[PDB]
Image 1 (cartoon, rainbow, N blue to C red):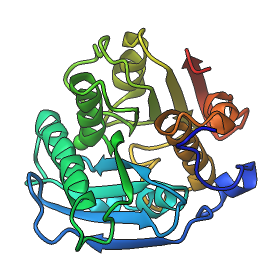
Image 2: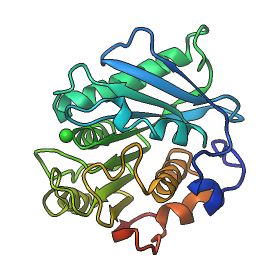
Image 3: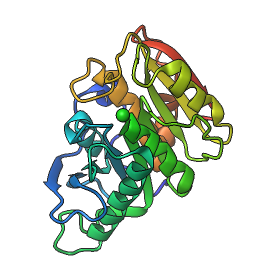
Length: 262
Ligand SMILES: [Cl-]
């Protein structure tokens, strides 16, 4: 028995729906430490401790741009913290530091008897996500903290394209027509630079820079893939190996690549 496997056996329909099987509650962090603000989403009875994921927005953006991931992932068995940065103009390195600080506070709250997530988190199992500069920050977080178990940035933005040291399983969401973090000069070179890890590249057909944000028109496919990736690698849950590693074979995807996934 995989001690980290949670919830009923997955189906395409259960992964494509707006929410998974778990009931989700949330709270705003009272005294954020090391970042601007945060909302914690958690499942009320996942059947055991679950991993934690920290999600960071992009330049000038706030929690609303990435908020949909909170309920979506939490409803499948994760504690998710979506954060506002100290300043909306923070750079990827600062975003990475605040992302890790948010994860540290989730771990601290896990040991605080007054917190709603008291005893709900397996603090040894954590992941990182984020949009644009927050996606670049997620990759920096993975490079600097190889104990992280999964990463799934979307339209990542960073001055470098060489993340060759990353050993964390990394799923890159890309948007075909991105004019802010262009695929050919950012997302794809970042993907190609990683030779040590399970990795995946999923490009949304005709998508703009915000193609993976709250309110996007591909929440069924993007949500399915994001949850499947997190489940497969944060929980070592091989029930999700096919969903995580498969080509969707969908006209909504203009480019799909994967390596070392199974
Ligand atoms: Cl950005």
